[PDB]
Structure formats: structure tokens, C-alpha cells
Figure 1 (cartoon, rainbow, N blue to C red):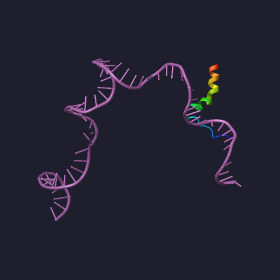
Figure 2 (cartoon, rainbow, N blue to C red):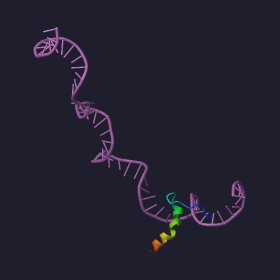
Figure 3 (cartoon, helix red, strand yellow):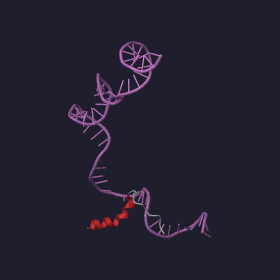
Figure 4 (tube, chains in turn blue, red):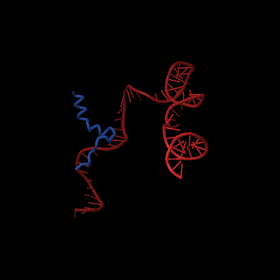
Length: 30
DNA sequence: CTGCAGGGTTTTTGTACAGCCAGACAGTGGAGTACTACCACTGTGTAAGACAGGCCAGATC
């Protein structure tokens, strides 16, 4: 199933890390 | 269908290495900063009526 997902605005940095890891990598690559 | 209970799910939340830059700390001697009282001194209240006594005008007899 899964937990009721995040609403942005509420967290500290490392949930944020794989929240965007793949886009930051696409950016690095660009 | 409700109730709770093993675990699932994905996701949190932080600890784990190790290197490293930033800016705070502390000094200074005083700079010139910034914020402080202090000083006399101000601006906005804004127009009518009531009441007493005179006394002359003029009606009434």
C-alpha cells in the first residue's frame, strides 16, 4: 500500500535527497 | 461489518564513515558608528442664545 505521502513544505533535507536524486543527476549529466 | 495483530508496502530520520570550507571566536585602538535623551515648544478645540433693565413708541381711554 504505502503511507499517506508527503505534502512538500514539511521536511528537512534527506527525504529531499531521493525525492530529487535522479533529476539532480540528469542535471549533472546536462 | 467491526475489533486488533503478524507482516507487507514506501518512506522517513538518523547514524554511520572521511575530507573541508565558512564564519564565529578573541584582540585591538579606536575608529566613526548608531541610537539616546534633552530642549522648548506646538496643534486640535471658534458662535449662538438668555436675561436684565432701560425707555421710547404708540395704541387704548
